[PDB]
Amino acid sequence: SMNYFVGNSLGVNLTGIEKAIINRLNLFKEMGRPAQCVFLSWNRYLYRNAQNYITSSDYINMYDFFQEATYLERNEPFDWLSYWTDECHYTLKHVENSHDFRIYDQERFLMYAHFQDPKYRILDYVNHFDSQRRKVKRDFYDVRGFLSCSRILVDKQQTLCEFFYNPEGDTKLEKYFSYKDGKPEVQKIIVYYANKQYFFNNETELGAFFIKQLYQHGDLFFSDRNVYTAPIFNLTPESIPVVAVLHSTHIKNIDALDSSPFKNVYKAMFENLSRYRAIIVSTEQQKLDVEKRINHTIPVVNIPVGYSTPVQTLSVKLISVARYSPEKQLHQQIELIKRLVSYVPKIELHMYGFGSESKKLNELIQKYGLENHVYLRGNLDQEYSDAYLSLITSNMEGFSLALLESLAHGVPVISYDIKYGPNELITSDFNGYLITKNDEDALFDKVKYVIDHPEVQQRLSKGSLAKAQQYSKASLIKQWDQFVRLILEHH
Image (cartoon, rainbow, N blue to C red; front, side, top):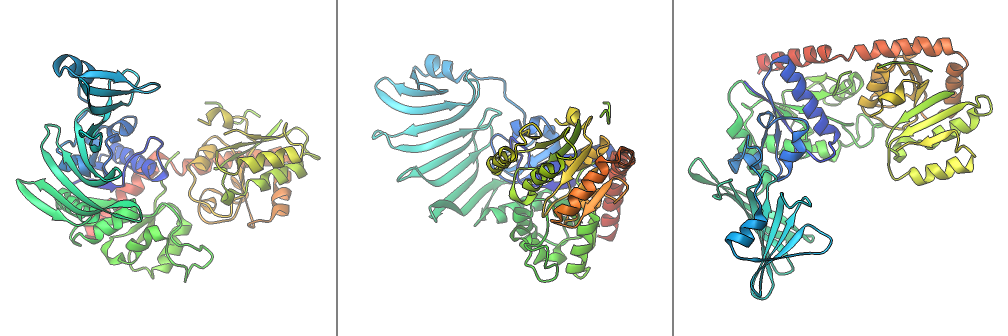
C-alpha cells in the first residue's frame, strides 16, 4: 500500500503547498508508511528542483510516467558542441552576452541553441528554422539530458502541437492546441501506453487516467493542489479513496461563515464532497468552521502542516516575520513603535519579509524619524536568540511555520485574534496574548505591559517553549499514523 500526495510541481523557490507535501513525505518515511509525492504538470526542470529535497524514488511526475522517465536520474554530461563541430561538421557562432550558439551547415542557418550554464553542459532548447528563416520547431531538453518535448509552431510562433518522447526518442504523448484569449489551450491529447493508444480532450482527463494507472487496492490519495487535483479525482471512481487537504481559508469572505462562496480554488472539491473520504485542515479553529459549513457530511480533521543553539540571551528587540503585503498591516507596527519609543527609547523592531509594501513602510519609518528603531530586514536562527517578542497585526492569517519556529526558540507573541493560525499557536497568558482585531490601543497596552514586566516575558517565553513541543515530529507522526489507519478501515 502506497500513500500518494498529489500536488502540481516543485518550483525553484518552494511554495507553502510544496513544502507541506515534502514535510509530509519525510514524516511518512520516518513513520515507515510508504509515501510518494505525485506531480502533474510537464516540468523538464523538476528533477533539479527536487534534488535538494526528495530522491527520485520519492516522486512520480505524470509526464515522466508516460514518457517512461519515472525514477530516471541525470545522464553523464554530453558535449553537444563537439558533436555538432566534430561529428556533424556544423559551424557554431556564439551569441554575445549569452549561452547561446547559432548553428550552420556552411552558409545555411539551421538552429539556435540555448544552454542553461556558462559551461554549455546543460542544453536547454534548440530552435529549428526553414529556408525562409521561419521558426518551425523547438526541442525542449530535460535537465537530465534527454529531448523531452518538440513543439511545432505556426504563424507568429504560435504553439500548434507538441510531442513528448521517452529518453530513447519514441513518441509517448501528443497534444494539439487552439488559441483562446491569445493563449494556446489543449484540445486533444494522444497517449501511447500499454502498447495501445488513448485519447483525451484536456489534461484533467489525462490526470484522471494517470490516477487510475497508479491505484492498487490499499493505496490512499491526498488532494493537495485542489484547483487541479479536485477536477481530476472527480473524474475517477469512488472505489479510489482520496482525502482533500486545504492549505488556506476555505471561503472568500471569512466574516460570512454560512453564506460566503467557497474559494474558487476549492469550488470543485466542495461541490462534490461525497467523493472525498475526509478533509484535512491545519487548525482546530478551521476544522470547526468547515465541519459546521458542510453539515458534517464527511469527517474534517486538523493536522498541522509542520512540526517543531542558545536561546533568550537578551536593547528591547521586537520582531515581525511576515510578507510585506497589505493583509499583514505592518504599518500598524510602525505606529506602535512611534508611540512606544517615548517610553522605551532602546527599542528596536526588525521586520523580516518582502513585498510590494516596502516603499510605503520606508516612507513611514522616515516620516516618524524611526530609522534607528525600525528595520526592514528583507535562516532566522540567530535572529531569534535575542528577540523579546513577536508581533502579528494581520487582518487574516494561516497556520504559520514561522511562528512555530520562533516559539521553539522561546520567543513569545502578541497577535490580533484573526483566523486562522494565531489561536492555534497562542494561548493567552501562557505563550502570548490575543488582541481584538485592529485595536491598536489594546495592542500598545499589552506590548508595553510585557516590556515593563520582564518576569512576565520570561513566563511567556517558557510557555512558548512548551507550546512548540506540542508540535513535535513524534506527535505529528502519531496524528498522521492514526488518521491513515482510520481512513483505510472505514473505506
